[PDB]
Image: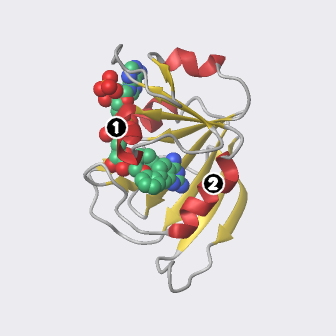
Amino acid sequence: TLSILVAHDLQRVIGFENQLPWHLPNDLKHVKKLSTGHTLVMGRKTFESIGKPLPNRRNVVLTSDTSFNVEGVDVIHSIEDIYQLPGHVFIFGGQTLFEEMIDKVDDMYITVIEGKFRGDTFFPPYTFEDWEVASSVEGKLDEKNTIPHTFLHLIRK
Ligand SMILES: NC(=O)c1ccc[n+]([C@@H]2O[C@H](COP(=O)([O-])OP(=O)(O)OC[C@H]3O[C@@H](n4cnc5c(N)ncnc54)[C@H](OP(=O)(O)O)[C@@H]3O)[C@@H](O)[C@H]2O)c1
Ligand SMILES: COc1ccccc1-c1ccc2c(N)nc(N)nc2c1
């Protein structure tokens, strides 16, 4: 299965200055739960943002840099290489990867951040005419998690 994994706000902002615009520990827990034991594919900027491969899953980085050879990371140089990756593969970002893959994936695990943030990078527009809501779950709010959010699983119709 090939899936998108993304958190975006009410206006589809995903990032600002190579970081996330929000602090939301529960979304990181969600990412951990979904992708542990599986594969993440990310663009080079997203990788450099996170700084190191995420533990307990396969980290694959897409880059044109033929000098990229980082410990604990697999490298690919073409979108086409993604389709040769075994198992459950999650497209992990960023904007460029999401733009290249939204028409290709089977489903999407979206955390809708129910706020309006300043962004410089966006998830591409999409319509519920194309996507079935397999599940929609409101995130619980507390002292550490203060922004309303909804976990959506969308499956291509
Ligand atoms: N909210 C979220 O769910 C989420 C998730 C991830 C990231 N983000 C945010 O997204 C932003 C980064 O997005 P971005 O679009 O600037 O960067 P990106 O997608 O992370 O990385 C772009 C880089 O990926 C490589 N790449 C992409 N397609 C390629 C292809 N077909 N062939 C070869 N290389 C390819 C290139 O690397 P080279 O230049 O090295 O060739 C390109 O410059 C940041 O703000 C980050 O915080 C948000
Ligand atoms: C730059 O992105 C991050 C920085 C620090 C911690 C976590 C993230 C990060 C990266 C990718 C993500 C992705 N594809 N989906 C969701 N729902 N959350 C993410 C969070």
SS label for mark 2: helix
For label 1, being within 8 Å of ligand 1 is answered yes
Q: Which numbered disc covers residue 45?
A: 1
Measuring 46% from the left and 38% from the top, which residue is drawn there?
A: 98
Measuring 37% from the left and 32% from the top, which residue is drawn there?
A: 44
Q: Is residue 95 visible?
A: no
Q: Which numbered disc covers residue 32?
A: 2
Image height check: is 18 above or below 40?
below
Question: Which quadrant holds residue 106?
Answer: top right
Q: Is residue 68 left or right of residue 107?
A: left
Q: Earlier in the sequence, mark 2 or mark 1?
A: 2
Report x, y in % for residue 2: 66, 33
Measuring 64% from the left and 16% from the top, which residue is drawn there?
A: 84
Q: Is residue 139 visible?
A: yes
Residue extending farthest to the front is 71
Report x, y in % for residue 66: 36, 13
In the picture, the quarter occupied by the C terminus is: top right
SS label for mark 1: helix
Which amino acid type is shown beneath numbered disc 1?
A: Lys
Q: Nearer the viewer, residue 102 or 65?
A: 65
Which amino acid type is shown beneath numbered disc 2?
A: Lys
Report x, y in % for residue 125: 44, 46
- How many numbered marks are there? 2
Tell me the CA gap for discs 2 and 1.
20 Å
